[PDB]
Length: 100
Figure 1: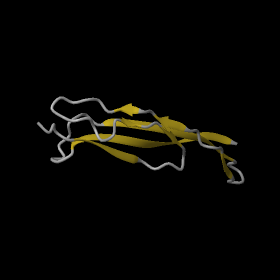
Figure 2 (figure 1 turned 180 degrees about the vertical axis):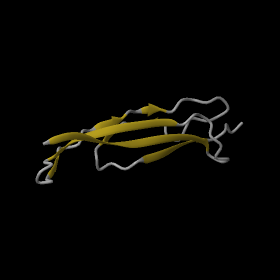
Figure 3 (figure 1 turned 90 degrees about the horizontal axis):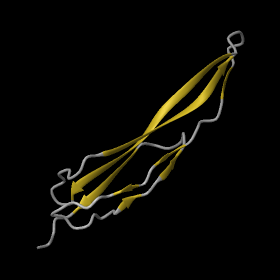
Figure 4 (figure 1 turned 30 degrees about the horizontal axis):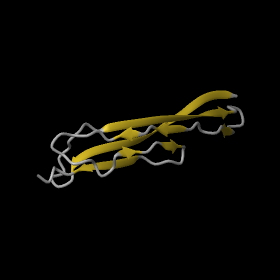
């Protein structure tokens, strides 16, 4: 009965770009969540059993105001539950320059 732990990381990245030029107007926000489960192996029979994975959450991220730009298309990126079935995500928040 040998016990070990398996872990994996699921990540959401938020990008902030100019709507037209696609230049990044803010630093990326990177949200890694590391889930785990127990692994039990009988070394005589070779039988391996796995426990349930933990769960996580990508936190809400408010898109800040940037000088010279209108309000972002997405004012806030919502928090999201992360499970072992979740895939990595990328979200792009877009800012358009003032009309002036």
